[PDB]
Image (cartoon, rainbow, N blue to C red; front, side, top):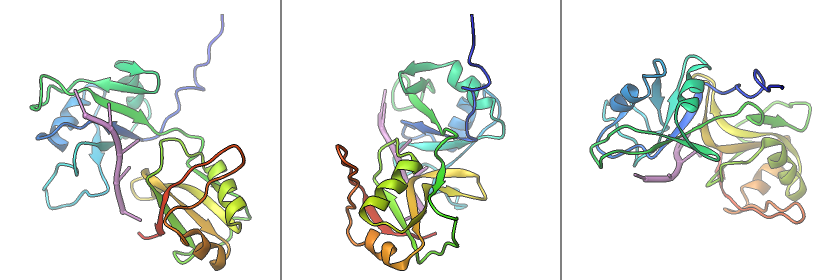
Amino acid sequence: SHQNGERVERYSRKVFVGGLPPDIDEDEITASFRRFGPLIVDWPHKAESKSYFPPKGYAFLLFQDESSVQALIDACIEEDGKLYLCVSSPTIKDKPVQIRPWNLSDSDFVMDGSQPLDPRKTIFVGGVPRPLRAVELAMIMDRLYGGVCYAGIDTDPELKYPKGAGRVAFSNQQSYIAAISARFVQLQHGEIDKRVEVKPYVL
RNA sequence: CUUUA
Protein backbone atom coordinates (compact mmCIF):
# COMPACT_ATOMS: atom_id res chain seq x y z
CA SER A 1 0.00 0.00 0.00
CA HIS A 2 0.96 3.68 -0.38
CA GLN A 3 -0.24 7.16 0.66
CA ASN A 4 -0.25 10.80 -0.53
CA GLY A 5 -0.40 12.61 2.83
CA GLU A 6 1.56 15.83 3.54
CA ARG A 7 1.08 16.63 -0.19
CA VAL A 8 -2.73 17.03 -0.43
CA GLU A 9 -3.46 18.74 2.92
CA ARG A 10 -1.99 22.18 2.11
CA TYR A 11 -4.48 25.07 2.24
CA SER A 12 -4.85 28.83 2.67
CA ARG A 13 -5.86 30.69 5.84
CA LYS A 14 -8.94 31.77 3.83
CA VAL A 15 -11.99 29.76 2.78
CA PHE A 16 -15.18 30.79 0.98
CA VAL A 17 -18.46 29.77 2.60
CA GLY A 18 -21.48 29.91 0.31
CA GLY A 19 -25.21 30.07 0.92
CA LEU A 20 -24.94 32.13 4.14
CA PRO A 21 -28.61 32.22 5.23
CA PRO A 22 -30.80 35.33 5.70
CA ASP A 23 -31.48 36.98 9.08
CA ILE A 24 -28.48 35.63 11.06
CA ASP A 25 -25.01 37.11 10.53
CA GLU A 26 -21.32 37.04 11.57
CA ASP A 27 -22.02 35.82 15.15
CA GLU A 28 -24.06 32.71 14.30
CA ILE A 29 -21.46 31.42 11.82
CA THR A 30 -18.64 32.21 14.27
CA ALA A 31 -20.60 29.83 16.52
CA SER A 32 -21.34 27.22 13.79
CA PHE A 33 -17.77 26.55 12.59
CA ARG A 34 -16.34 26.90 16.14
CA ARG A 35 -16.52 23.09 16.53
CA PHE A 36 -13.34 22.94 14.42
CA GLY A 37 -11.51 25.61 16.45
CA PRO A 38 -11.87 29.41 16.71
CA LEU A 39 -12.50 31.37 13.49
CA ILE A 40 -13.37 34.79 12.06
CA VAL A 41 -15.26 36.00 8.97
CA ASP A 42 -14.96 38.95 6.57
CA TRP A 43 -16.29 40.31 3.26
CA PRO A 44 -15.24 43.23 0.95
CA HIS A 45 -18.19 45.35 2.18
CA LYS A 46 -17.31 44.84 5.87
CA ALA A 47 -17.29 47.95 8.10
CA GLU A 48 -16.81 49.10 11.70
CA SER A 49 -20.43 50.38 11.70
CA LYS A 50 -21.54 47.08 13.34
CA SER A 51 -24.30 46.80 10.71
CA TYR A 52 -23.28 43.18 9.92
CA PHE A 53 -24.91 40.87 7.32
CA PRO A 54 -23.27 40.60 3.84
CA PRO A 55 -24.97 41.97 0.67
CA LYS A 56 -27.14 38.82 0.30
CA GLY A 57 -25.97 35.40 1.47
CA TYR A 58 -22.28 34.57 0.93
CA ALA A 59 -19.15 35.22 3.05
CA PHE A 60 -15.49 34.24 3.50
CA LEU A 61 -13.78 32.90 6.64
CA LEU A 62 -10.35 33.77 7.96
CA PHE A 63 -8.37 31.31 10.10
CA GLN A 64 -5.26 31.23 12.30
CA ASP A 65 -4.18 27.63 11.71
CA GLU A 66 -4.00 25.57 8.51
CA SER A 67 -5.26 22.43 10.31
CA SER A 68 -8.61 23.99 11.29
CA VAL A 69 -9.76 24.12 7.65
CA GLN A 70 -8.71 20.47 7.40
CA ALA A 71 -11.11 19.25 10.12
CA LEU A 72 -14.06 21.31 8.84
CA ILE A 73 -13.53 19.99 5.28
CA ASP A 74 -12.92 16.35 6.33
CA ALA A 75 -15.84 16.02 8.80
CA CYS A 76 -18.64 17.26 6.49
CA ILE A 77 -20.65 16.51 3.32
CA GLU A 78 -19.10 16.68 -0.16
CA GLU A 79 -20.18 17.08 -3.80
CA ASP A 80 -17.19 16.32 -6.09
CA GLY A 81 -15.79 19.87 -5.70
CA LYS A 82 -17.68 21.63 -2.87
CA LEU A 83 -18.88 20.71 0.64
CA TYR A 84 -21.82 21.40 3.00
CA LEU A 85 -22.45 22.02 6.73
CA CYS A 86 -25.61 22.57 8.81
CA VAL A 87 -26.50 25.73 10.79
CA SER A 88 -30.26 25.39 11.53
CA SER A 89 -30.81 29.02 10.46
CA PRO A 90 -34.20 30.85 10.88
CA THR A 91 -35.00 30.73 7.10
CA ILE A 92 -35.78 26.99 7.05
CA LYS A 93 -35.19 23.83 9.11
CA ASP A 94 -31.53 24.04 8.01
CA LYS A 95 -29.22 25.85 5.54
CA PRO A 96 -26.64 23.65 3.80
CA VAL A 97 -23.87 26.29 3.72
CA GLN A 98 -21.07 25.47 1.28
CA ILE A 99 -17.29 25.40 1.83
CA ARG A 100 -14.50 25.94 -0.72
CA PRO A 101 -10.92 26.73 0.46
CA TRP A 102 -8.20 28.51 -1.53
CA ASN A 103 -5.35 26.41 -2.98
CA LEU A 104 -1.60 27.08 -2.93
CA SER A 105 -0.58 26.85 -6.61
CA ASP A 106 -1.89 29.79 -8.70
CA SER A 107 -2.34 32.71 -6.27
CA ASP A 108 0.00 34.83 -8.46
CA PHE A 109 2.30 34.67 -11.51
CA VAL A 110 4.90 36.73 -13.42
CA MET A 111 6.17 36.64 -17.00
CA ASP A 112 9.03 39.16 -16.80
CA GLY A 113 11.80 40.33 -14.41
CA SER A 114 9.10 41.55 -11.98
CA GLN A 115 9.46 45.17 -13.13
CA PRO A 116 8.16 47.97 -10.85
CA LEU A 117 4.35 48.22 -10.75
CA ASP A 118 2.03 51.24 -10.44
CA PRO A 119 -1.77 51.76 -10.14
CA ARG A 120 -1.54 53.46 -13.57
CA LYS A 121 -0.37 50.23 -15.27
CA THR A 122 -2.81 47.75 -13.69
CA ILE A 123 -6.26 46.47 -14.68
CA PHE A 124 -8.94 44.71 -12.61
CA VAL A 125 -11.00 41.76 -13.88
CA GLY A 126 -14.33 40.58 -12.40
CA GLY A 127 -17.30 38.33 -13.19
CA VAL A 128 -14.76 35.49 -13.36
CA PRO A 129 -15.50 31.75 -13.09
CA ARG A 130 -14.05 29.74 -10.17
CA PRO A 131 -10.84 28.51 -11.93
CA LEU A 132 -8.48 31.02 -13.60
CA ARG A 133 -4.85 29.87 -13.07
CA ALA A 134 -2.63 32.98 -13.10
CA VAL A 135 -0.20 31.19 -15.47
CA GLU A 136 -2.71 30.95 -18.32
CA LEU A 137 -4.36 34.27 -17.42
CA ALA A 138 -1.08 36.05 -18.20
CA MET A 139 -0.35 34.03 -21.36
CA ILE A 140 -3.75 34.90 -22.87
CA MET A 141 -3.40 38.64 -22.18
CA ASP A 142 0.03 38.32 -23.85
CA ARG A 143 -1.48 36.84 -27.05
CA LEU A 144 -4.16 39.58 -27.28
CA TYR A 145 -2.39 42.61 -25.75
CA GLY A 146 1.22 41.69 -24.89
CA GLY A 147 3.46 43.67 -22.51
CA VAL A 148 2.23 41.66 -19.48
CA CYS A 149 4.46 41.54 -16.38
CA TYR A 150 2.28 40.22 -13.53
CA ALA A 151 -1.11 38.53 -13.05
CA GLY A 152 -3.09 36.87 -10.24
CA ILE A 153 -6.21 36.87 -8.07
CA ASP A 154 -6.98 40.00 -6.03
CA THR A 155 -5.43 39.81 -2.54
CA ASP A 156 -4.80 41.94 0.55
CA PRO A 157 -1.41 42.04 2.37
CA GLU A 158 -2.84 43.00 5.80
CA LEU A 159 -5.47 40.23 5.98
CA LYS A 160 -3.33 37.82 3.89
CA TYR A 161 -6.35 36.66 1.85
CA PRO A 162 -7.80 36.75 -1.69
CA LYS A 163 -10.84 38.93 -2.46
CA GLY A 164 -12.01 36.97 -5.52
CA ALA A 165 -11.79 38.52 -9.00
CA GLY A 166 -8.32 39.23 -10.44
CA ARG A 167 -5.82 41.86 -11.58
CA VAL A 168 -3.17 42.09 -14.32
CA ALA A 169 -0.23 44.48 -14.62
CA PHE A 170 1.87 45.56 -17.60
CA SER A 171 5.38 46.92 -18.13
CA ASN A 172 3.92 49.43 -20.64
CA GLN A 173 1.24 52.12 -20.35
CA GLN A 174 0.17 51.24 -23.91
CA SER A 175 -0.69 47.63 -23.03
CA TYR A 176 -2.55 48.85 -19.94
CA ILE A 177 -4.91 51.15 -21.89
CA ALA A 178 -5.29 48.31 -24.42
CA ALA A 179 -6.52 45.94 -21.68
CA ILE A 180 -9.16 48.40 -20.35
CA SER A 181 -9.99 49.34 -23.96
CA ALA A 182 -13.27 47.38 -23.82
CA ARG A 183 -15.57 46.08 -21.06
CA PHE A 184 -15.10 42.56 -22.48
CA VAL A 185 -11.53 41.45 -23.22
CA GLN A 186 -10.65 38.58 -25.56
CA LEU A 187 -9.37 35.39 -23.91
CA GLN A 188 -8.73 33.29 -27.02
CA HIS A 189 -5.77 30.90 -27.19
CA GLY A 190 -6.79 28.54 -30.02
CA GLU A 191 -9.64 26.03 -29.46
CA ILE A 192 -10.43 28.14 -26.35
CA ASP A 193 -12.59 31.22 -25.64
CA LYS A 194 -13.59 33.16 -22.51
CA ARG A 195 -14.89 36.66 -21.66
CA VAL A 196 -14.90 38.81 -18.51
CA GLU A 197 -15.66 42.36 -17.32
CA VAL A 198 -12.85 44.91 -16.82
CA LYS A 199 -12.21 48.22 -15.06
CA PRO A 200 -9.23 50.43 -14.12
CA TYR A 201 -7.63 48.94 -11.00
CA VAL A 202 -8.34 50.68 -7.69
CA LEU A 203 -7.67 50.08 -3.97
C1' C B 1 -29.60 27.44 -0.23
C1' U B 2 -23.57 28.62 -3.68
C1' U B 3 -18.38 33.48 -3.91
C1' U B 4 -15.96 39.82 -2.83
C1' A B 5 -12.03 44.72 -4.46
